[PDB]
Length: 130
Image 1 (cartoon, rainbow, N blue to C red):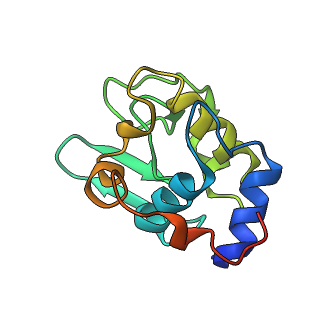
Image 2: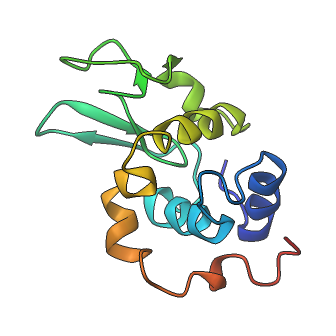
């Protein structure tokens, strides 16, 4: 599924993401935007380390979800990576919350530092009623 901007904003608010671990909804929106373009079935193979990024938040298979083919893999979140390709993003949200529970917070995603950190992120939630 490819979410509409405001549709996603409201869904994330309803799932308790606004202010989760000090992270505003606008920042989570900025992350999803640059990570997948609000696309739940987005996948990205990292040829260099043989891991794959799954879903709307591009969660990596070496640490957060299990896909069986990732060398030296860990399953901190404890999810099957398949769960992160569903239209219903409840599992991708529980996974995302787990990622930010580590000291890096939202900085775990390099894309966040590149295009979200220290920018005006209001544009991602303006007009959505959240």
